[PDB]
Length: 80
Image (cartoon, rainbow, N blue to C red; front, side, top):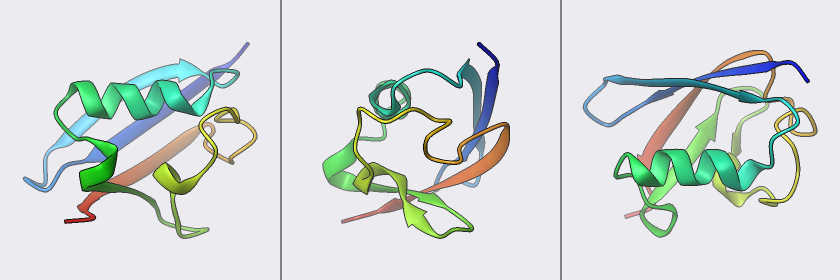
């Protein structure tokens, strides 16, 4: 029960920030960024290394299961 600390950079270049259960399902993060106004159908959620569009990952997996732990910076970007 330890701490995933994510920093999402917005298109404005500003930094969304918050912590989750590393045991927390991925959909949770999906919702967090969505609630802050950044919807899946419209935005790629990018991890640098290994470069993956996290949105494209199965929402059921854990942040632990997806190497999102314990100190990542992510990137939102228009799927247009």
